[PDB]
Amino acid sequence: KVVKNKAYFKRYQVKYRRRREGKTDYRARKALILQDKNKYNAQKLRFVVRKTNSQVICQIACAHIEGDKILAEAKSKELIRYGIPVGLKNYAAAYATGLLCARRFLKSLNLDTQFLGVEKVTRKPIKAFLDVGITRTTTGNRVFAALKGACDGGLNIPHGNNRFPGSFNPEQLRKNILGIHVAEYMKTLQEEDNDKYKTHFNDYLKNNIGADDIEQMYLNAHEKIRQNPKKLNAKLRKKRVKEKLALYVELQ
Amino acid sequence: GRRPARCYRYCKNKPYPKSRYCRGVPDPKIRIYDMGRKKADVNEFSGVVHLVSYEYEQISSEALEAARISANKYMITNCGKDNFHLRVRIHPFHVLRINKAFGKPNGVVARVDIGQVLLSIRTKENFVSKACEALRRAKYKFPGRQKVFVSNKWGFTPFSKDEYQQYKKKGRIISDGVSCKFIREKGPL
Amino acid sequence: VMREIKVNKLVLNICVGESGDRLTRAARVLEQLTEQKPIFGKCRKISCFVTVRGKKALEILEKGLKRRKNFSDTGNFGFGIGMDFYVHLSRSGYRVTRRTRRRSKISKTHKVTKEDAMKWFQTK
Amino acid sequence: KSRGKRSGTRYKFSKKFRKHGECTANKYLEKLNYGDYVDIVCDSTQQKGMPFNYYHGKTGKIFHITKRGVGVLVNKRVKHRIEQKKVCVRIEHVRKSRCNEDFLLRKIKNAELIKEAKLKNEHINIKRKTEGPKPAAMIKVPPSKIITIEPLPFY
RNA sequence: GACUCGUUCAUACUACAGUGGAUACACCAGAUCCCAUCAGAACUCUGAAGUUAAGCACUGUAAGGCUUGGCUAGUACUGAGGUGGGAGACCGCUCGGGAACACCAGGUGAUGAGUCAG
RNA sequence: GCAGAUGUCCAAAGACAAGCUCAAAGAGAACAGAAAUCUCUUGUAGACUAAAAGGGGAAAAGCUUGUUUGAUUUCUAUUU
RNA sequence: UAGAGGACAGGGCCUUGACCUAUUCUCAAACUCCCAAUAGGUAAAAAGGGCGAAAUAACUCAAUUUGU
Ligand SMILES: [Mg+2]
Ligand SMILES: [Mg+2]
Ligand SMILES: [Mg+2]
Ligand SMILES: [Mg+2]
Ligand SMILES: [Mg+2]
Ligand SMILES: [Mg+2]
Ligand SMILES: [Mg+2]
């Protein structure tokens, strides 16, 4: 038997568009969105972090019957403007992005003076919830870096500490946000297999970013962020069909 | 062995077929359904007589079988064995039951409508009278008012004769055995 | 260029009886052969196997080698020895099938096929 | 004999053909208030909060809203008397009814009309005039386009 | 030109083709570190040498499906009426309501918020 | 009336989350066959969901894994 | 219920099959893509509704006023 019969097609229920594409959970999403129906007018802001292959995307989203509404938005490729080029999928970079997004949101609100949050690295705060959406939450994830960054900015993002690297080890987390792990890796590469190292951190090399400097650069970036943010209709088709038949006839 | 058949004439009771909720029900007497040159082409036989019930009645399987037999034997006697094709176009699914409380199953019956046909013969346009005769003979073995009814169609195929001819002339109609399929200018190439 | 036809995954397979220490022995043997810890396959514990990628897998295949039929319609193949080797061939971008995120279907022209597999075999 | 809480529900609670799955995530954003009229349409994909067989399709005023609940005042005819039943449901089943909104629209339009009338002092008749009899007309038809009819012979 | 969150949840699907990649998506390169396994396949982390080959986008197909429309058909069925017909089975009429499959024809998306590149 | 079912079973078959996809069919791979396990392709559920039958269920409500005891105390509004 | 068209199992390229493909006959109280008629429910505004202000709160919100 052919499995994909006419009958099968007739039966077939198509998934939701996003689910089909493979981008949203829906099960997760509804839970994230719906808040208590006796709390009418309470928006519930979700902090969306996407870890795309060569960027991180941090949005504050609101949710409405017609479509979601993005209040604040930051992509990791803005960080060039703030004096951090290369390593944009880096945990540090993610953190920075998160922070930036938070800052942007605050600016949009007109409420930046009250919520400074954690100054440098170690009224009730504006609340939001992490939409990690589809990437599984393993310990040392990059979305959690972003979340942390956001927190360090203004936002109350309720979180447990189990998913920061080495967990609760704060030193490790600190290292990660500085970029220190990356630096260490670079150093190790330099020490053994130099050709490989050259191949690998090519962009970094071109920039002229040695190991030691990376942390400093990240710090500077953080400081900067803190400071300021065509079709054919029926007739044509028919004509085409006719032409093909004619050609077939000719061939015959 | 059996009841009168006036017992099970009318279609009281809802239909009640062989399934999970019946089980121990004996077989229909009728097994063959269609006979006489069943393997014939569509182009072979043009003449088609129907035997239409003008009655909302039931028709025992046994009766049906008898009718079929009558049709066949007569045909054999008159024209050749391979000059006709006798479809019985009605099947016995609704089972009857008997008490001797709820009844235990006992024989099957082939419930019919005012419009629908019982038997259809399909023969060469020469032997239509014979076919008609056969069908009328058969009729004496059903209950209720049937009417033998010569059709405008080509032979079970749903086209009129002229129409069929026309189609044949411009090659829009593939013949299987008995059934014919009409090309619609639709699928891929 | 991306339409090269790498070996995706080689799977060494030892079906044996019903877990009476012979299975353990088989597992040990497998381990010795290839640096992977083996995994057990259950009744519907009867059998061991190991999945291998990359250079190691290739090496295994090469040693293992020491037919037109033993290729599948889908363009994998296998052979036996005691072991069964099954090699599963793919092209780059096989990940699109199997990732978690926007998992999708590979186009027909990018699935490997029998003839292609045969060709590949002939080449290596 | 067998009057369980989900009897005669082989079809009431069966999800319709090519609409299985679950309730869409945007259905949880329907705003409800103490007074909104509300259909109760049992999505049997959620098994929590499933209101009884009978209230499927029946509208009611919301009298109570909760975390994920909605109490609905629904009428039930009970032999000799209709009575108010306080059907506590989840949000998945409760849909916002549309009857009230037809009225609302009309109200809005009527306000505008009233304002307009006042602007000029006129006796505008608001109330919906039902389909009365048609007025006199003179319908031009060519003799060409008047297809005469006879009954049909039998066939 | 692309992307993120969405909305409707097949006009959005599927199959087989064709066309496209400045930026983007993606595949792809690697395993020190967080992490994850039988397996760095997945997941994670760190990358940027390549490539549109796939994904994705776009278009095609007397495509299947889906969906509007006509047509089936005032056919089937039916609410009320009947000291109507019919031995009954059932069938007309009066006041009303009125399908379905198939078939034929068209269509194959639309869109809210935000960002990015030029 | 019809076809049945109940007087139970469950520290998981409860709770939560994570991951995963099931039946079947096909084409393959020593011993291995109509059946063992493995691999891939197709797979709207045709599996499974304690026990009738019916609904529901696919990044699950199924399967595997991790962690647990909300199978807790008190009280309402109620539905059948 | 029938053949038609196709590409695995047995005998001496043919026959018997099963299996696919497109058909075909007839069916269902405990089948359903679809789906009437009738029956049913809510609504059709002054104890109310609009659009506003200002109060009150220990609720709600990031927002002594974010809203309820
Ligand atoms: Mg007698
Ligand atoms: Mg009866
Ligand atoms: Mg291409
Ligand atoms: Mg089509
Ligand atoms: Mg889960
Ligand atoms: Mg029928
Ligand atoms: Mg029925």
Image: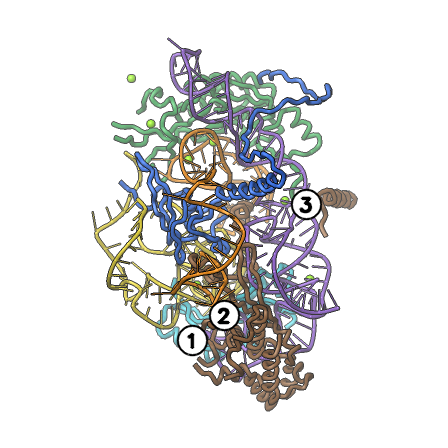
Chain colours: A brown, B green, C cyan, D blue, E purple, F yellow, G orange
Give the letter of the chain under mark 3.
Answer: B
Q: Are marks 1 and 2 in contact (CB under 8 Å)?
A: no
Looking at this view, is F12 or B15 the one in front?
F12
Location of mark 1 (residue): C27
Mark 1 Cα shell of 10 Å, populated few (<14), some (14-19), many (≥20): many
Give the letter of the chain under mark 2.
Answer: A
Q: Are marks 1 and 3 in contact (CB under 8 Å)?
A: no
Mark 1 or mark 3: which is in front? Answer: 3
Q: Position of residue B31 (x, y in %)?
A: 43, 31
Q: Position of residue D133 (x, y in %)?
A: 57, 24
Label 3 to label 2: alpha-carbon separation = 63 Å
Secondary structure, mark 3, is loop
Q: Which residue type does callout 1 highlight? A: Ala
Quarter of the picture containing the C terminus of chain A is top right
Mark 2 Cα shell of 10 Å, populated few (<14), some (14-19), many (≥20): some
Report the label total.
Answer: 3
Looking at this view, is D54 or B152 the one in front?
D54
Looking at this view, is A211 or B93 the one in front?
A211
Label 1 to label 3: alpha-carbon separation = 55 Å
The relative height of residue E62 versus residue F38 in the rendered view (above or below) is above
Judge left or right: residue A32 versus residue B176: left
Quadrant in the rendering for residue B126: top right
Q: Any atom of ligand 5 within 8 Å of the CB at mark 2?
A: no
Secondary structure, mark 1, is helix
Q: Which residue type does callout 3 highlight? A: Leu
Location of mark 3 (residue): B189
Circle number at residue A126: 2
Residue located farthest toward the bottom when viewing the structure as drawn: A191
Q: Position of residue A130 (x, y in %)?
A: 50, 68
Give the letter of the chain under mark 1.
Answer: C
Quadrant in the rendering for residue A56: bottom right
